[PDB]
């Protein structure tokens, strides 16, 4: 409770297996849309009905649906098109993987990968990674797992996720007066020190 | 992300009124003389390796301390990041030139670039110098008249210069 | 998928024989268990990396079928 | 928002590359198409008040009961709100004409239209047939090329409502 | 492959919605550039043999070292491969012109270009030289918009090589 | 997915020879008639909800069994699935129409679509009937000449009829 | 569907753990309250025809313009559809009573209610005030907690509509 | 914690919906049964010291070697610490009786129980026997349904240990 | 992270010069005496649970205030968190011991533990006390000449003590 | 964050969140018995600086004669002076990689981002490849035993990276 994220930890994990009837699916959609889009408001016009139909039929798993949403126009228009690449990498980590970035090597690698292979490859590097399949796998909606100690994490990852979280109410709009600027530009490359120009 | 049309539309919406006659005339004139803008953008896209290589040559001959051991563009990794930054900035300048508006530039490449460079210790003065060198090397290409119908494009030159100056002054 | 290479997607049937369970026992089922046999869909754009990932995991595949032609 | 130029830049940017030929050709097509759209915007802007009044009267004709006391339409305030709503749709149609894209509609009207129509019990068919009236009225206001563009946007808004 | 039309289909598909005005405007902008593209395709298809032989000779003159024995260029079969490579590049440029998009060029030559060039140790600068040659005489074989479309496609191929 | 341009390039690269003169003539003719195809696809896009509503009315009025309990389109969930599938079919048909190539419809929207319904027990002949009713309404809305300059487009009508009936046969 | 037992078992299987006290305890509550459900449903099934006829009559009094020729409610087949729809809603409300969970109501009426009510231009308010009449008439048919169970379920249906 | 109320609220929140009738039914059952559970809690709190001391003695009787000198159980501090641990367990059983769910048990005792027992060489069998004795004695203390609820919670803790 | 070799390499690179004879001799000496370093790391890894058990016993006997209800390590879950933290810190000190450089320690392990523990509310002073308790309980295992060839390892004892003290001083 | 046997074992242990078992200790012992030939090879390669770098430069000139005359990269005094500087860099990082007994220094300091710099400065990798071939030929004579094998191993890694 001294950390903001009391309720997020208490939040149940959600799973969607093949013979899901109705309300398991309806709850899964709300959980996915709440987490992936960073608690941002998603109007009924923007909701992808075809991806939901594919998920309901079972052609794509929950992970494939997450990948499609990450490649959707809402994800781009909010996190990619309006922010620098640092903020995009941080948002990708926080949403698709549930953890903050651990070091600067991640930013360098992901920025080079984007510049060389495109947004689709950039996103696939997240979902198809071994880390996502370990923690979540095909059938589990991603959750904020950085608040507990994650095997192999850096000392700073918990603090960085605290910086990214901003309460259960707060969200990663890009509708702010600031314009969705990055949060961890100096924390990642200079972890401990503080400087004044 | 905006272009000049969407800027005018958004400003009108904040006022709450239909687009004025003068604003419509300006947008129509922008569209009419926008084929020169297409030529300029194609010139920036087509020659981009030439601009980048020339700017790198003049910068590193001019500023030797970077490519020295312990310099900030010393190893191949830092040099590649340098050239990649030049390429990205030129890419977004061409984007802003086609759009007629610097929103995409100041919104994707410059909202957090000075802080990033400072937190990496990179000399922002040298980055601004690099942007100016790309500006010169790219004007040398835009003013070329080969392959195109001769005309007057002074306004486009001034606009591209202002985009390069926006980048160079919001980095330094 | 916009290009000619992107289309011609492929369908893979995967079995989770002991070579996968023996690894995941040592890693741990922090993802709740499922059935052994399951069928996966893959486009040509990621057909190789998906197969590499499946073989790294330890599963044995049955067949791959070209959905498009 | 989302126009031809903006969609071109966003597509060329997500892939992280310079603007190749196809992007420039689409840009050229939009730039040359911009003229008919501009005088279409001129025509609708000039005929603002007449179009709004006609749309309101078409509303009160096709749905006679709405004007009865005890419903949505009764009360001078509600008539003024109807006129304001029609003005809003018309203005954003002219905006989308000028931008040569469906951006301004999808942002300021279509985004979240169903939720706000449902909350206030507003009937979508009201604005659907008011837009039908405007659609018919630009049958005479605009002729030739620009008429196709104006009709395209009017009907896109209608399709969004329904 | 990726054309203007196919990109329009893909971008309207990803949102799972009908083609709005912007998609149709992009398609129309393609079509209004289709006939100069076909003119250019005819004009630089009727000059295939002279252009390929001249490009091979230009590579030889600019690169004298790729002629004598002790290297790749020396050899009858090697030079037949040179001519066939130049013909391949020219044919794919014709294909891109006809499609009015870099699709065929991208997915045939550009996709995997660096790995192929390294593994077979074919210096790209050979092909930049040949494409600059082709640039030079398409400056005169074509005039007007078709000239520009050629120049643009050959330049995009060059930048892919470089 | 393919369009007729890329299709022709596909045969041309299969033979390996350049596109023949008659091939270029055909493709130029197709491009010149392109604006009529754009009007066709715009008529299909614009009036899609009307097509769907009329097709659903006629289809359900023809076969009362679907509406009734035990019918496959009985509950609100399955009725909404029916309507959504119908509009998806119309959307992909319009895609194919604009592309001028059946590949867009055949290669992705119709792969498992036929067997999926059998897995769900859906009567596929009802799907075919719905497709034909959609075709009839689409032709009604395409024949309309209001707001468009008159002309001859019987080729477009025939091609759209082939697209619709071929989708039905893929389902049938 | 989803009853209390269904929710219990689904959550337990989701957590990968046995039946501890909490969900057995809620199951006890469900079994205990299953009786007012049974007599409420039996009384509702006793009064099918009267309830549906009164409901459609209340609709016609509330929406007289619907009955006019040229409108949705004109004709004999349309009124038959009114009776059929009200019968469907009543049957699903009794189903939700018997199951003592909202489930059947959700997965038969609510599941895709908006899409269907929009495609066929059916109005939610018709059914809302039909269910209001059903409230009014059940206010006398039932007694005790059967009333509150029936009313909570009708309220669920109405909130789904509005 | 994880009560009936809190689990209800959390599952409704995750689905982003209000509380429909099923969760209110579960809450009603919980409120109806609060009286027996609170009765069991007050009976356990009344006979606190006797239960603790009897549990410790039963552990010693079934585990004689634990009383041997130079070993884990020997020592006044370890006797006191046994008493403290059993007091903790009984406290949390009363907590779970009051909260009408295994919230406090899971939060405090069970969460992390296994690895902390491993890191201290505390045999779970000791606490299993202590809880078996407490179950036996609360069979004497509590009659009726308070017995059932208590035994549910002691058995849940026993299952967690075993 | 760095080992000693990589640190010397990085300094020689910043000076832009080859590795001197002196630095080569220091690294050769490190390699020759790296066997004892392996033995020290093996001692740390083989007795990790014992070291944690001793440290926790002595800490919670020294500080009954933590385990006491309402305290920090009370709720039987925070106690497991405490034991896990002991695990992590000992693991990172063993890594820094094998490497020969404290880079892993102060990079991966303890940049933010100060503020992490201030945010979570845990008393950092007790954490530092626990770390130096781990130091004391680990030195007895590190010095243990049982089943290991007898030699001199004063430098390794000093190194391990310095790493534990660095961790304690940072977290404190 | 370079790559070294010690770094590999530490990173694999850390990523799995466990201690270093007997396997990582086996690997570290292997590296520590590596390091005497590796360091003495680096010493022998450092002591013989100027001959190596000058011979590699002249190999670049001889094997690529067309670079020498004007109109090419090799013309202009600063160009060959800075060629000597480049070969000095490559030799230095070979010595660093011998000392570290891993390809960490080569990768991080030369190989990563090599192709982009070579492209954007119009430098043929073949010049450097055959210069490294000459240095390989010389280390075939300055060094003997397993030191020759390991120096050739790192030079081969660099050549494969260039190619
Ligand atoms: C730490 C790893 C690293 C290396 C190795 C490296 C090499 C390097 N090669 C460069 C371009 C160059 N490289 C050469 C080398 C040529 N000279 C001729 O005698 C030969 C045929 C040939 C060498 C075999 C030349 C002439 C340039 C000049 C291009 C320019 O002026 O930009 C430059 C730009 C310096 C300048 O423009 O003055 C560097 C720093 N950079 C690095 O960060
Ligand atoms: C990729 C393109 C695509 C296709 C081809 C598609 C067909 C499709 N229809 C489905 C269900 C359905 N589809 C229908 C419609 C049919 N049954 C009735 O007889 C109607 C007359 C007839 C309409 C043509 C119905 C009633 C269901 C519900 C079946 C069920 O829930 O068991 C499903 C499974 C769940 C879902 O997606 O909603 C698929 C995949 N969906 C897609 O996203
Ligand atoms: C898409 C918008 C965007 C851009 C373009 C961007 C630039 C950027 N430049 C970076 C580092 C760098 N930037 C430069 C370039 C500068 N240093 C040299 O001295 C030159 C004077 C000058 C270039 C002209 C260099 C050399 C580095 C490497 C520093 C390092 O790796 O630590 C980094 C962090 C590490 C990496 O990416 O490898 C970013 C994110 N960030 C963004 O969000
Ligand atoms: C596929 C991408 C694309 C390109 C490349 C393109 C170029 C293009 N340039 C044009 C004219 C022109 N182009 C230019 C621009 C050039 N003249 C100036 O002197 C500068 C040297 C330079 C710009 C800095 C000008 C000034 C005109 C004439 C505009 C006028 O006054 O009508 C035209 C109109 C017809 C013509 O006169 O040829 C086109 C289509 N259009 C496209 O759709
Ligand atoms: C359709 C797309 C396509 C392209 C673009 C292509 C280029 C190409 N040309 C090749 C043969 C070749 N081509 C050349 C010609 C080069 N060397 C010199 O003579 C000239 C300066 C220069 C020509 C401009 C040579 C020497 C080879 C033999 C391969 C080798 O040396 O390793 C090869 C190796 C396999 C073969 O064809 O025998 C490729 C991949 N191949 C394709 O299938
Ligand atoms: C921005 C998107 C867009 C629209 C809205 C569009 C409509 C359009 N239709 C046109 C001509 C035409 N359109 C048609 C097709 C119609 N003729 C009959 O009414 C048939 C019922 C129907 C076929 C379905 C015909 C036959 C022509 C005349 C041929 C021609 O001018 O090329 C033209 C060129 C002549 C002009 O309008 O001044 C346009 C711009 N084109 C576009 O690129
Ligand atoms: C899952 C249970 C279920 C429900 C709830 C349901 C409602 C429902 N009512 C329908 C028809 C209808 N229902 C009505 C009745 C309305 N109009 C007026 O008469 C009244 C004010 C009001 C009723 C009180 C009308 C007029 C139609 C015809 C709509 C049309 O064809 O345009 C339809 C379309 C089916 C068809 O075209 O035959 C549905 C889906 N259907 C179901 O299977
Ligand atoms: C929140 C709830 C909670 C629980 C359940 C709990 C159990 C618990 N008992 C402990 C000590 C202990 N517990 C026991 C076990 C008892 N002593 C013997 O007389 C009996 C045979 C036996 C019980 C039947 C012993 C022997 C110790 C001393 C361990 C030591 O210091 O070596 C410890 C280690 C902390 C310390 O050293 O004081 C814990 C965590 N602590 C909690 O905060
Ligand atoms: C894979 C795991 C592994 C390890 C760790 C390992 C260490 C190791 N220790 C050795 C002897 C030794 N071990 C030590 C270290 C000890 N002597 C001091 O008194 C301390 C009590 C203590 C370290 C703190 C010393 C000093 C030697 C003799 C070498 C010398 O003269 O320094 C040797 C040489 C031959 C032998 O006795 O086995 C090895 C290889 N070997 C392995 O296969």
Image (cartoon, coloured by chain):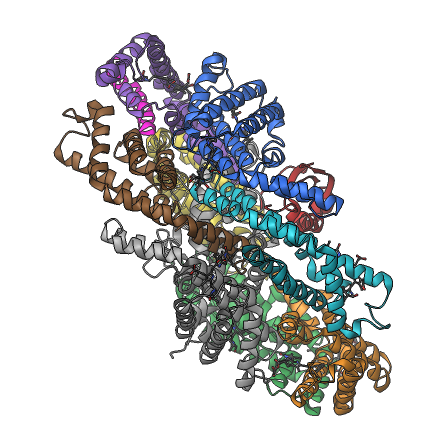
Chain colours: C red, D brown, E cyan, F blue, G purple, H yellow, I green, J orange
**Residue F68 in view in this figure:** yes
Q: Give the answer, above or below, for where A149 lies relative to A68.
A: below
Q: Give the answer, above or below, for where A111 lies relative to G17.
A: below
Along the line of sight, the residue nearer the viewer: G47 or G144: G47
State yes or no: residue G137 in magenta: yes
Would residue E152 appear left or right of E131 to someone viewing this image? Answer: left
Along the line of sight, the residue nearer the viewer: J70 or G126: J70
Magenta-drawn stretch, dominant element (helix, strand or loop): helix
Image location of residue F81, percent across then percent down: 48, 27
State yes or no: residue C17 in magenta: no
Give, as a single range, the part of the protein colored magenta.
Answer: G133-162
Image location of residue J125, percent across then percent down: 72, 74
Would residue E68 appear left or right of F126 to someone viewing this image? Answer: right
Image location of residue F108, percent across then percent down: 60, 36
Would residue H123 appear left or right of E71 to someone viewing this image? Answer: left
Image location of residue A52, percent across then percent down: 50, 37
Along the line of sight, the residue nearer the viewer: D151 or A195: D151
Q: How many marks?
A: 0
Q: Give the answer, above or below, for where F48 lies relative to A78.
A: above
Would residue G86 appear left or right of H90 to someone viewing this image? Answer: left
Q: At x 51% / y 32%, what residue is drawn?
A: F88
**Residue H128 in view in this figure:** no
């Amino acid at each position: 409770e001294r950390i903001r994220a009391l309720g997020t930890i208490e939040a149940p994990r959600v799973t969607l297996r093949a013979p899901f009837t109705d309300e398991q699916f309806q709850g899964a959609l709300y959980a996915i849309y709440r987490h992936i889009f960073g608690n941002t408001y998603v109007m009924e016009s923007e909701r992808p009905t075809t991806a939901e139909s594919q998920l309901k039929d079972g052609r794509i798993t929950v992970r494939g649906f997450i990948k499609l949403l990450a490649k959707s126009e809402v994800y781009r228009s909010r996190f990619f098109q309006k922010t620098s690449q640092n903020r995009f990498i941080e948002l990708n980590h926080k949403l698709l993987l549930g953890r903050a970035p651990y070091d600067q090597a991640e930013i360098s690698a992901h920025l080079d990968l984007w510049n060389t292979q495109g947004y689709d490859a950039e996103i696939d590097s997240y979902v198809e990674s071994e880390e996502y399949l370990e923690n979540f796998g095909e059938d589990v909606i991603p959750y904020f797992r950085g608040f507990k100690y994650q095997t192999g994490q850096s000392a700073q990852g918990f603090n960085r996720l605290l910086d990214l979280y901003g309460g259960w109410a707060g969200s990663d709009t890009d509708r702010n007066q600031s314009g969705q600027v990055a949060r961890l530009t100096n924390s990642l490359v200079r972890p401990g020190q503080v400087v004044e120009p | 992300m905006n272009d000049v049309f969407t800027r005018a539309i958004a400003q009108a919406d904040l006022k709450g009124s239909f687009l004025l006659e003068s604003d419509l005339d300006k947008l129509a004139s922008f569209a009419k003389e926008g084929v020169k803008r297409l030529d300029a953008v194609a010139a920036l896209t087509n020659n981009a390796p030439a601009i980048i290589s020339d700017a790198a040559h003049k910068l590193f001959a001019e500023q030797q301390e970077l490519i020295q051991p312990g310099g900030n563009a010393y190893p191949h990794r830092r040099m590649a990041a340098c050239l990649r930054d030049m390429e990205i900035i030129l890419r977004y300048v061409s984007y802003a030139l086609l759009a007629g508006d610097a929103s995409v530039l100041d919104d994707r490449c410059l909202n957090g670039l000075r802080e990033t460079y400072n937190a990496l210790g990179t000399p922002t003065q040298s980055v601004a110098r690099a942007v100016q060198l790309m500006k010169d090397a790219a004007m040398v290409h835009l003013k070329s008249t080969a392959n195109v119908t001769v005309g007057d494009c002074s306004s486009l030159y001034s606009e591209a210069a202002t985009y390069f100056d926006k980048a160079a002054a919001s980095i330094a | 998928a916009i290009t000619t290479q992107g289309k011609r997607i492929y369908k893979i049937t995967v079995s989770e024989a002991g070579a996968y369970a023996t690894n995941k026992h040592r890693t741990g089922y922090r993802a709740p268990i499922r059935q052994s046999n399951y069928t996966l869909t893959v486009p040509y754009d990621r057909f190789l990396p998906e197969m590499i990932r499946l073989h790294q995991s330890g599963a044995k595949i049955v067949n791959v079928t070209s959905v498009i032609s | 928002s989302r126009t031809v130029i903006t969609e071109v830049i966003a597509t060329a940017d997500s892939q992280g590359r310079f603007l190749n030929s196809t992007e420039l050709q689409a840009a050229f097509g939009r730039f040359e198409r911009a003229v008919p759209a501009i005088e279409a915007a001129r025509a609708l802007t000039k005929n603002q008040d007449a179009l709004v009044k006609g749309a309101v009267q078409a509303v009160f004709k096709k749905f006679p009961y709405v004007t009865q006391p005890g419903e949505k339409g009764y009360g001078d305030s509600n008539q003024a709100k109807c006129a304001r709503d029609i003005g809003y749709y018309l203005r954003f149609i002219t905006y989308s004409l000028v931008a040569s894209g469906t951006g301004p509609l999808d942002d300021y009207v279509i985004a979240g239209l169903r939720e706000v129509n449902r909350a206030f019990n507003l009937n979508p068919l009201w604005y659907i047939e008011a837009l039908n009236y405007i659609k018919g009225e630009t049958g005479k206001l605009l002729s030739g090329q620009s008429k196709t563009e104006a009709l395209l946007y009017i009907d896109h808004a209608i399709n969004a409502l329904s």
